[PDB]
Length: 223
Ligand SMILES: CNC(=O)[C@@H]1C[C@H](N2CCc3c(ncnc3OCCC3CC3)C2)CN1C(=O)c1ccc(CN)c(OC)c1
Ligand SMILES: [Ca+2]
Image 1 (cartoon, rainbow, N blue to C red):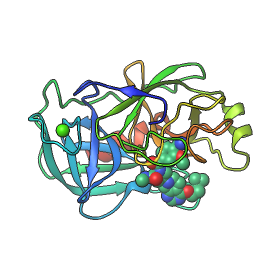
Image 2: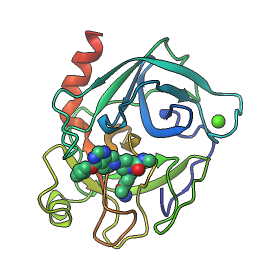
Image 3: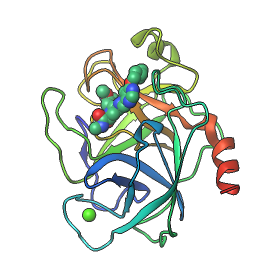
């Protein structure tokens, strides 16, 4: 997160860190045994880390649970990132508490101007690199689809939205992908891609979760 602020420990209790010996992606807890992340985060040997604040320190509220099954969206395209969403089932249920809590799925799609909370452990610099270890937060609005498509001609699909600031300075960045975009208590987005971080006219691009709620619910109910 570039241009954000320190969330505060366990203030984003649905935020997870996906760890394969190191933090590689964010995710969102959606019930005790399932996490939503980006399909581009798919890999073997995932451990889901819940209840984290500083990812380099065991502070006493963490739960570490291995993934048992990963389900990449049936239509995910790795060349274009269309349908950039995946479900991860945990080997055992997380114990739900004040520090480890699920986030609601949308019941409808959110609009341009809706304010959201984006969070993650990614790079905090727009030029060069610095990783914060504690969770960072950013308040950002959803941008109109026309400004998103104009910023990224030929690359934005009906399954994506832009959020952030066209003037630059505030954005998600390397190591935030897979993590949450939450608006009025609903997981509307997944951190997906962009061109650089916090550059003018290059806002972050996010998977449009509302289009996937039917698939998420059906997949969870059958697995
Ligand atoms: C260490 N983790 C990372 O670096 C991940 C990998 C992810 N990338 C996306 C493109 C892509 C991937 N995997 C196959 N193909 C990819 O792109 C192919 C081209 C299609 C049009 C996207 C995976 C971008 N990452 C971010 O954390 C990130 C988050 C937010 C922003 C917004 N400023 C950002 O901006 C550059 C980057
Ligand atoms: Ca921690």
